[PDB]
Every structure is written in C-alpha cells, then in structure tokens.
Image 1: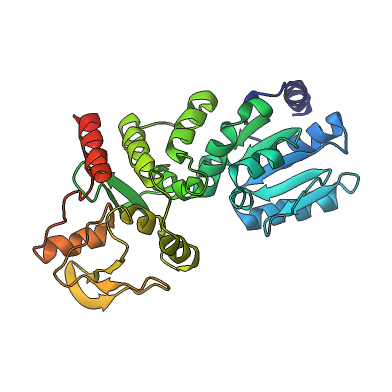
Image 2: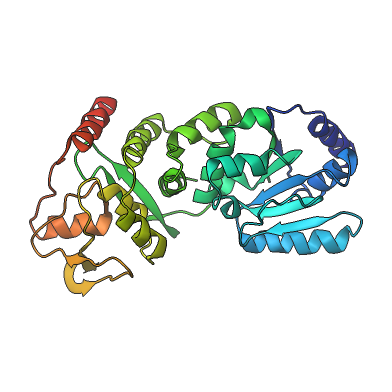
Length: 333
C-alpha cells in the first residue's frame, strides 16, 4: 500500500552515490511507474531520473501513460538516436539499447548526470540489458542504482575445448531464464571499448546479486570473451557486422581469429543436408563444399552439416586460439 511505498521512497532517496538497492514490487502499480514518480517528487522536479526498460514499445507506452497521468512532472523518451549533451529534467524513459550506442566514457558522462538509475524488468536479461548493467557497474561508485522486478523455441549455447569452442542453436523448451546466449550476444557491446562484457557481468552480479550463476559457463564465456577482444577487429569484418542481416554478427568477430571468409553451410530439412543455403547481406561468402572452415563459433546446423557430410572441424591454427583451447580444457578438467 502507501505505507510500504513511503518507506521504499525514503530508503531510495537517502541512498548515497556508489550504492545499490534491489526492489520486488509485486502489486500494483508499481513500478514502472509510481516509484520513480514518488522519488522525483521527493528529490525535486528539476533533478534527473533514468528508468531503463527492455522493449522500445514498452518505454514509449510508459512515457505516454505517465505524461498524461502526471502533467506536473517532465517526462522524456530515449528510444531512437543519441540526444547529444542531453540534460532533460524529469523522468527519462529509455531502452537499454539506446545507451548501447555510446562509448564507455560517453556512457559514464551520460549516466553520472542522473540522480537515480532504475533498472526495470531486469529478469528479461536481454543482450542490451546485460551489456548496460555490466558496463555501468564499471563506474557504480558514481551512481545510485535501483533494480526493480515484478513449449517454445529458444537459442542455447554449448562450450568446449575442441574448436568450434562456441556452438549456438534453437532448442525445444518450456515457457517462462537461461541468459547464456543473450550474454554471448551482449559481448558485441564491448568490442569497440575493449571491455570483456562477461567479466563485467560476473563483477556486476557479485555486487548486485540479480541472477543465478553457472560458474563453469561464466568462466568459459570469459576466456572466450578475452579471445574476442584480444586484437583490434579488422575494418572489413567491422563493416560486414555493421551492415549484415546475419542473425549473430558476433560469429563473424569470433571467427576472424581463424578466417576472414564467411562460409555458407547447406540448410538442414528434417535431419538431412539440402541444396539450400541461407544467404545474408554483405558477407561475400563461399559455400561449404567439402572444405570446412576453421570456425571458433558455429551454429548447431553448421556442426550438424559437418557431421552428416562425414567432415571434420579444423583444430586451432594460432597461439591465441590454441591458448583459449587449453584454458577451456583446464577449467573443465
């Protein structure tokens, strides 16, 4: 009721910079909604508060609702292009993806200017959400952060010391969370900054205690993430990733440690190899044929085609890739 909200607001409003609070708001309303509203009415209307929402549509929807409901409070929406030198005063409703456009120093300069940062629906664990949480935690000392919470076919990952070290693919499962695939995709958000997103996630989760952890999986993912950012990404690969409609461009970034040429593996209908190939834009790819590429990162179907055809994946071809393999073997052992 109002008794528990006033206590929650007073606990939030008295937080010092460098502090974190987790909130479970089971009933009502809420969250998104009345919590940052009550916080801003307490700290002052011209102070800045950020509310991070996973879906862009959900952000626009809260923004519309709140601005009509509370005309006395200023509201801002950030779901498109970066508003350069943004200093807008009320509650800012932004998607996590909006902040994924910023470099680490730009991100910090933007973030520190908010009195409070509300991480809404953290349980969704989207790649933009996982990247932002890990990235902002790197300067958490400078922030007041509050995390709030209320069959199907999904991508899963397999990790091994035998190359391809990463294998991703759809899996049949019950309904709503396994965030490993989203964590792997989130890694793309630290390439340009030379940030290990896995390390940032592990460090954030140790302080914030938001997610359950599979220690072996995190350790393996962190070893692979170090390989990912070990060298500057080639400009040719950077351009392809920025422009392709490929569902996992990070595959291009991981594979560049062995090959610059993407390969088109024949599609699998039922449990058999077809004369069909999935062609994505900007790749300038060759078909598999009988020459299997030295992939670090493969898809379940790419691996399946290799098996069905009687082919073998190559072994690590350089020091870096041989070392990732022995590090992964040590960790499993």
